[PDB]
Image (cartoon, coloured by chain):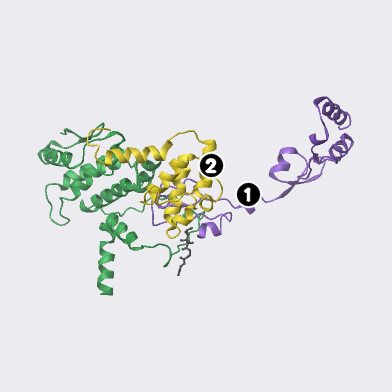
Chain colours: A yellow, B green, C purple
Amino acid sequence: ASLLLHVLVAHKLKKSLDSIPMSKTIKDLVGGKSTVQNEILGDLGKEFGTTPEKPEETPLEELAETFQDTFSGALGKQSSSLLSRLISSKMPGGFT
Amino acid sequence: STRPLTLSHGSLEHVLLVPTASFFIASQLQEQFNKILPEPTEGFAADDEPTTPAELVGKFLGYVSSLVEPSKVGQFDQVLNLCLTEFENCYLEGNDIHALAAKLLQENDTTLVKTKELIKNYITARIMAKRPFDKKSNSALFRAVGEGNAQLVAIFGGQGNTDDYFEELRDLYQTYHVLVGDLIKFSAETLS
Amino acid sequence: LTHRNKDGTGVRVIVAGTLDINPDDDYGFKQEIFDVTSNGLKKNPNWLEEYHPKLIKNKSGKIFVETKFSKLIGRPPLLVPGMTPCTVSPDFVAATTNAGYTIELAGGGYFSAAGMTAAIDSVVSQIE
Ligand SMILES: *P(=O)(O)OCC(C)(C)[C@@H](O)C(=O)NCCC(=O)NCCS
């Protein structure tokens, strides 16, 4: 979950997998625009199902654990749909 | 006296009943259209390629609507008027376009960018083929305000709600070009 | 922002400017304006009216505070809860049950099925 969460957040911020430090709240990373914040929470909602209460107030590091329990290396709805785009929309010209 | 034509992209199609009177027009648009839209890829995930039959017909309505003139009666007017009347009777079942855009978004693996263009295409088409919105729509909410169930209040926002408000004006103008074009134009003159 | 100020007053906000989908379905998007089916007229809960406490009578003519909870148990919506010393006694559990009020026997003062079964049996012997 600690990798998958990092990637889902990294992808929504148009930012590199190390420019996001895990020891930092979601409302910290997108403090300005509140749209992106909720849009991240909507994505974690689809991806891992059940969330804590005020997930954008607990650091990703801390929140990754809470998911790690009830999730089992499942890509699920959102991540699968992001890879389906990544391949087809980028130019693995023939190889799916 | 009719004749079948099949708009298709990879695995999905809409079968389209063109009066043979105006077929040599439509089949020339079909091949011109069938080369612009890209190579089918699994899931139909890439932003350009449509994901359902409903989107594919919409992509067409747009491409045809981009060749009509709003005054000059050209060749494509009756072509477009029999893509609309198909699209409205298959996929809208006498609802609004927005009610359809919703369904696709929670059923099928469409995105927002994918469903924004479908609303652009349909509403462009409706106006390029002189069919202006004049029917007092059967909106559940407004049937409910007449009956006296629902009370409505309008509220308007202000500054502070976004970093770039101007992307809201751009996205609004990109999609409802054919409804707001006149109000935008009026403001631009009235401020200038 | 207005939605969160008045969640639970019986007011639905519709964001007339954007088309998206609310997972929670707390507030609406553009669709709700245009939609023709019953999926355009949705109401939000009015907690003061949903869960308003009422009164109600028996054939005997004995009044009850009617709530979600009292409607299930047929007794007033007051429970003496499980307290280790206090509701360990089956003589207390019986008196409170007799009276007409819900009460927990307390596991915390029992050390074995045998011991508790003797307690539960002493309760059943005394209640109506
Ligand atoms: P997010 O939870 O941060 O979204 C809500 C919001 C902070 C954008 C919204 O509550 C907000 O705009 N707050 C202040 C209201 C405002 O912008 N006032 C206008 C300045 S004249």
B143 or A23: which is nearer to us?
A: A23
In the rendered image, the residue lying farthest to the left is B24
Q: Quadrant of residue B157?
A: bottom left
Q: Which chain's residue wears label 1?
A: C
Look at label 1 and name its amino acid.
Answer: Glu
Q: Secondary structure at mark 2?
A: helix
Look at label 2 and name its amino acid.
Answer: Glu
**Which residue is disc 1 drawn over?**
C50
Q: Is mark 1 within 8 Å of ligand 1?
A: no
Give residue A7's position: percent from left, percent from top: 41, 44
Q: Which mark is residue B51?
A: none
B36 or C126: which is nearer to us?
A: B36
**Which residue is disc 2 drawn over?**
A65
Q: Are marks 1 and 2 on the same chain?
A: no
**Residue B123 vertical placement versus B91 (above, below):** below
Q: Which quadrant holds the N terminus of chain B?
A: top left
C82 or B181: which is nearer to us?
A: C82
Residue in the image at 83% along x and 24% along y: C114
Q: In the image, which is nearer the foreground, mark 1 or mark 2?
A: 2
Give residue C57's position: percent from left, percent from top: 77, 44
Q: Is residue B109 visible?
A: no
Q: Does residue B54 appear to the left or right of A61 in the view shown?
A: left
Residue in the image at 44% along x and 41% along y: A3
Q: Does residue B70 appear to the left or right of B98 in the view shown?
A: left
Q: Secondary structure at mark 1?
A: helix
Give residue C82's position: percent from left, percent from top: 79, 40
